Image (cartoon, rainbow, N blue to C red; front, side, top):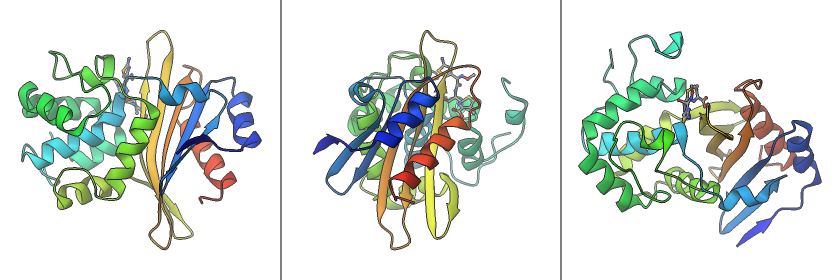
Length: 238
Ligand SMILES: *C(=O)[C@@H](NC(=O)/C(=N\OC)c1csc(N)n1)[C@@H]1N=C(C(=O)O)C(=C)CS1
């Protein structure tokens, strides 16, 4: 069941910011859509840095890296030695590009097709297909992927999935944990912003989300997290 959720308030959150966006929520066997541009939920976009979740899974599963490896730029914040988990937190593109080159094109295409992530097209450049195309994915497809990660239902080892989940913890309070990954594809004709993840409630219940919106260069990166938290509170998910 995919349905519009009844929410006047979340539509207004997107409107106030003069942006077009959608929030996709998956619980149990229900997907609900919120926001002011619900047609975005079935629209294909580059995954941008959200692909780091799948890149990490493939690399760990195939023993191209491990969680303790120290990998020795656009942002000064990237200009340092770091682990795969620290690269996840910082969205350090060059670390993920190095991992992708280790995986190589043959393995990468085989794995993305096996998973069926989005359109599953990687083309011929192994180091940037998730940033500039041809790989594209819908917000509904992203919520389904991350819900499977959260439930350890992807077709990877249980330990590898647990290790990637542990890299994704964003916030917690009152026993609720929020896991996820941001992405932003800048310097294109319509900028796309992502925040895809899940809430783990105190009893262990999982509520998955994918926020997908049009970005502007004037916005702070944190607008994605702010809109997500306001929306999740409004829905009583946190
Ligand atoms: C991931 O989305 C990644 N974004 C980029 O590398 C891009 N631009 O940043 C300069 C990009 C991807 S496709 C395109 N045309 N441009 C990182 N994303 C975040 C984030 O929080 O979303 C960052 C911390 C900066 S770079």
